[PDB]
Length: 499
Ligand SMILES: CC(=O)N[C@@H]1[C@@H](O)[C@H](O)[C@@H](CO)O[C@H]1O
Ligand SMILES: [Cl-]
Ligand SMILES: [Cl-]
Ligand SMILES: [Cl-]
Image (cartoon, rainbow, N blue to C red; front, side, top):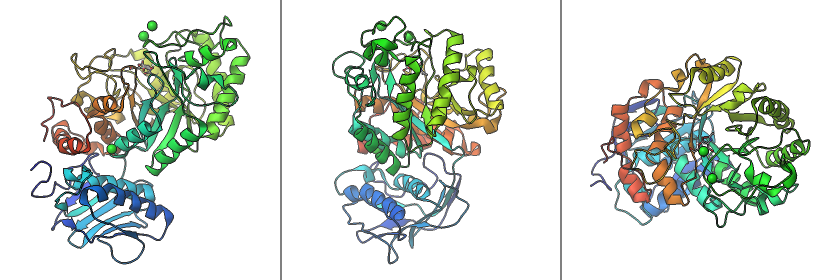
């Protein structure tokens, strides 16, 4: 009875592990007449309709959303110790109530509810149920404010609908930021009016050749809107000065030798560079960041800065000193890969650490020092949270430059004491990047993202006190029937006792 258990799943059996779980009493049961009662506000109703849409297919129930009466499922906004993202979930025969200070908290509460319900909830046709929700109370708040997932749409382009699909995958685990790698050597994915060829030419292909693609302003705005509806703040990235071949191939003048390189369809990195000694280079950067910032309601703008190996150190430093201010000029907070820590991060900047266990002390020191100087840290170790990394030598997709990364390794660590000498309060959170050199379709994205994606989300959300592999793997194993019913392919790691 994997699909429709006789009894409800444990109240604590959810990912991320909730801050506080107090089981008790009888469970709630959703029946054909259940109403979803929300506050008389747009934001409240919005979450109600979202919940209704998630449950209608499998239950076949009407589930009307209204601001009157005593619905069996109540979503209420009230004062409380739940911050901007926390919530309280009360379940019992009298009904299920989700309380939070803001919509995001209610949304997060819903993500927990869909896990309390049985696997059959993932089906698209009416199911027998029962639609039980374990009884008791859950009080939940996040450990870190930066819990993101990155999707590389430059190596292989993924359209609006495919991105919306990935957004729904991550929303399940309370991620609150979506980092989009919009440009690299194999493609430029965002239309820039001031530089038309970036998209029309720079976006014409991708890894392996053939058609590429890109987002028009309208498509990008739609992705941001959809992400916002799933409470994901979009963090766009335009990598510079390295990983810039798409742009360089589009405009000969940007190149040091004034010759446009061919469009790149390989899978290597580090060979491209904007010409730091040219003035046109900074007109280009200003134009792009200005247009991107206008399309970005979010607070951050990622300028990359990784593997600028065709850019001498001194030039890299000079380049970043010159471009960082451009971000603030357009009202945004700059973010960069940790290489930026060696190029004087401006005040308020954050750096994304993608180092490994084996990374040299000198490099780790430079990053820990930036943290001491006030730079916020986003942790995404290549040998931990890079979802494109192979599980073992036999994985049919992904890369292995950072070694292999099985499920336990990806989960078994603590962000607070990860980087030696780095102040714990400098750690803003974590990120799970999914690079696409080897992934060309949504199903392949799923196979590499799952089952590690949920784990990284827990590291960003759950209290350190709840972290434990032996008990987490049981909660992870329980997701199997849900993913199977949802049509979500995943790697059945031998380290997990799959349900
Ligand atoms: C910051 C960063 O990760 N840069 C590259 C990235 O462009 C590539 O897609 C990935 C694949 O694992 O390898 C990294 O070294
Ligand atoms: Cl989904
Ligand atoms: Cl090559
Ligand atoms: Cl390489």
